[PDB]
Image 1 (spheres, rainbow over the protein chains, first blue to last red):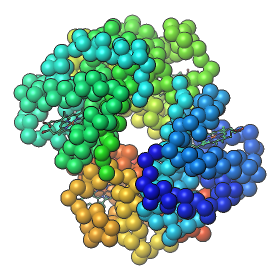
Image 2: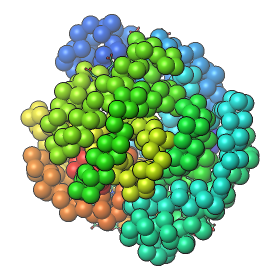
Image 3: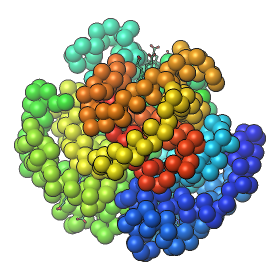
Image 4: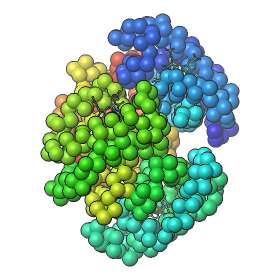
Length: 146
Length: 146
Length: 283
Ligand code: HEM
Ligand code: HEM
Ligand code: HEM
Ligand code: HEM
Ligand SMILES: [C-]#N
Ligand SMILES: [C-]#N
Ligand SMILES: [C-]#N
Ligand SMILES: [C-]#N
C-alpha cells in the first residue's frame, strides 16, 4: 500500500531483528489465549485449556511460524499484498470459513508482541507504520471472499 | 470496490428514474431523524426538534440536493471515486471534523430510501450493486483524513 | 432506550407485516448473503441458492423470533435468553454481523411497507433492531472473573506514578496510528509532548485508576464520565477499541515481564468493560 520511504525503512529495519520463529508462536498462542473463541478453528492441535497448555503446545508453535513466514513474504511485496495473499485468501474463505473480522485480532496481537519484545525501540511512529502494514495484510486476506 | 459491468449498468439504469431533488431531501431528513446525534453538525439549519420539522425544513432540503449531487458525480466517474471526492474529503476532515464512521450512516439511509421509492424493483442483486457504490464513496471521502 | 412511542411504532409496523413475517425473513437473509457475502461463512452447510428451501425455513424461524421480541418488548433479554447462548456461546458470531442483518431487515420492510415506512417509524425500528442485537450480543467475552481482578490490580499497581505518563503515551500512539480520532480534539495541540495531551493524559489514567479501585461497580463510578462521552460528545464506539489497543501497547512496552498472556487477556477484558460503561447511554 502507501508507505513513506521513512516508514518503508522503519518497518523493514525493525523486522530485521524479529525472530520470526519464536515470535510466530508468541503471537498465535496469545490469539488463542486472548480471544478464546478463535480456538474452535485449531482443535487439530490438541489441549488448549490453560495458557501454559497453549504456549507450550508444539502444534501452536509449529503453525505460528508458518504464519509469521507468509507475513514476512508479504513484506517483500509490500505494494501488492492482494496478489501475494490471493491463494491464502481463497483457502481461508472456501476451506476454512473464517469471518475476515478475525484477521484483525491477530493484527493487534502481533503488534503487542512487537511492543513487548522491543519496548523503547517500538516507538509511537514505528507502531503507526505497523498499524498500516497489518491492515494492508488483513484487507488482502479478506480480498478473495465471495 | 469493483462492480461488474452489469452491476454498473444496473446502478446507472436505476439512478435515471431517480429525482435527485426529492430523494436528497428525504435521505437527509432521515439521517437527522434516525441518527439524531448527527444533527449536532447542522445546528445552523434551524428547528430540527420534530420529524415533521426536519422533513419540512427548507435548509435540510437545499443541503440534500447538494449531497446527492455529489453522489451522481461519483456514479458518473465510477472508475475514480478518490479523485472526485478529494476536495470533499479534505473539507470533511479539515473544515468540518467529521469522524468517517458517520459516513456509513448516510449510505445506510440512502439504501433504505431507494428501496422505499423503488420497492419491488430494488431487488437483492440491485441492492448489492448499490452497497458497493456507497461503500466506495464513503471510502474515497475518508481518504484525505490525516 | 426504547420509548413508549417507540414501542407503539414497532408493534404497529410489525403488525402490518403480519403473515408475511415468514417470507420477509427469508428475503432479509438472502439480501444479506448477497450484499455482505462474508456472512456466508456462518452458514457453510446451507443451500444458499435463490429461493432455497433451507433458507425459507430459517427465515421463518428468524421471523418467529422477532415476533417473540416484539411481543415481549419490555423484557427482551428474558425472552431471548436461549437465542443469546446460541449466537454468543455455541455459534460465536462476531457482533458486527448483527448490523448487517438488521440493515437487510429494514431494507426489506421499507420495500414492502410503502405507506408505513415514515421517518419516525424508520427511526423507531432501527432502535428496536439495535436492542435485539445488543441482547443477542450481550453474553460474549464478558465478566471480570476474580483472576482478572487480581491481574488488573497486580499490573495497574505496577504502573503507579507512571500512570499519567502512560495515559499521555496512549493518547499519542492513538493519534498517530489512528488519525481519524483527532476529529474529537480539533482545537488541541496534539503535537508530541504538548501540555494539552499531557494534561489530558493524566485525567484518563486517573479515571482508569478509579475504575480499577471500583472494579466491581464501574457503572456507578463512571456515570458522569459515560454521560460526557455518550451524550455530551457522542464519540463513536469503535474509537474506544482504538484507545484500548494503544493502552495495551504502552503497558506492554513498559512492563514486559509482567505482560504475560494471562495478564494480557485480563487487561483486554477490563478495558473492554470500561468502554462499554462509557458506551451504554449512546442509544
Ligand atoms: C490474518 C492473518 C492470517 C494469515 C496471513 C494466516 C496465514 C495462514 C497460513 C499461512 C496458514 C497455513 C496454510 C497452508 O497450509 O499453506 C493458515 C492456516 C489456517 N488459518 Fe490462517 N492466517 C491468518 C489469520 C487467521 C485467523 C484469524 C484464523 C481464524 C480465527 C485463521 C485460521 C486458520 C486455520 C484454521 C488454518 C488451518 C490450520 C490447520 O490445519 O488446522 N487464520 N493461516
Ligand atoms: C456519505 C457521504 C457524504 C457526502 C457524499 C457528503 C457530501 C457533502 C456535500 C456535497 C457538502 C458540500 C456543501 C458545500 O460545500 O456547500 C457537504 C457538507 C457537509 N457535510 Fe457532508 N457528505 C457526506 C457525509 C457526511 C456526514 C455523514 C456528515 C456528518 C453527519 C456530513 C456533514 C456535513 C456538514 C455538516 C457539511 C457542511 C454543511 C454546511 O455547509 O453547513 N457529511 N457534504
Ligand atoms: C437480529 C439478529 C438475529 C436473530 C433474531 C437471529 C435468530 C436466529 C434463530 C431464530 C435461529 C434458529 C436457532 C435454533 O433453531 O436453534 C438462528 C440460528 C442461527 N443464526 Fe441467527 N439470528 C440473528 C443474527 C444472526 C447473525 C448476524 C448471524 C450470522 C450472520 C447468525 C447466524 C446464525 C446461525 C449460523 C444459526 C444456526 C444455523 C444452523 O441451524 O446450523 N444469526 N438465528
Ligand atoms: C478508555 C476510555 C476512555 C476513558 C476512560 C476516557 C476518559 C476521559 C476523561 C477522564 C475525560 C476528562 C473529562 C473532562 O474533564 O473533560 C475525557 C474527556 C473527553 N474524551 Fe475521553 N476517555 C476515553 C476514551 C475516549 C475516546 C476513544 C475518545 C475519542 C477519541 C474520547 C474523547 C474525549 C473528548 C473529546 C473529551 C473532552 C475533552 C475536552 O474537555 O475538551 N475519549 N475522557
Ligand atoms: C493462521 N492463523
Ligand atoms: C453531509 N451532509
Ligand atoms: C440468524 N441467522
Ligand atoms: C479522552 N481521551
